[PDB]
Length: 137
Image 1 (cartoon, rainbow, N blue to C red):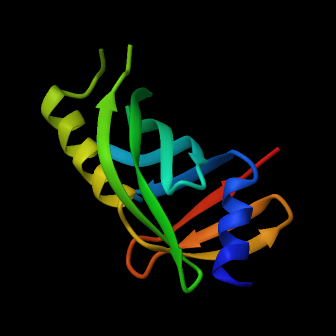
Image 2 (cartoon, helix red, strand yellow):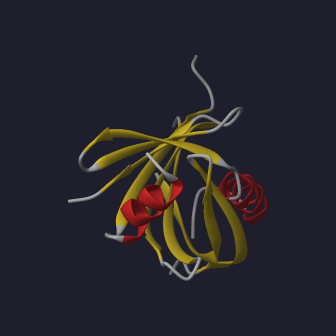
């Protein structure tokens, strides 16, 4: 589909997203990021993410995010302008949480190819950072 069709798909509804990163397979074992995101047609977006951390032997970081977005050649391009930890604490130190947040912020700006999984579900695939699932009700 065309870039303007893709833009209309993104702006016509609000979206939820899920991204899972497996860390170990045999200390932090896995990270689940669950988000709500709104793409506005003026090129702004707002995104609120719950970063769920699972270490073997559960803790959560809440992040509010704003920035600019664009569609080019069926890729979703994102340039975050600000992040704010609004989490209202854990079994992880403040340094650990800061490092996890830095990786989250890096993922937040990755360009992702857009593919339609079904009427309510999109797959966002990057070259080197995996896939995020975008879905609506």
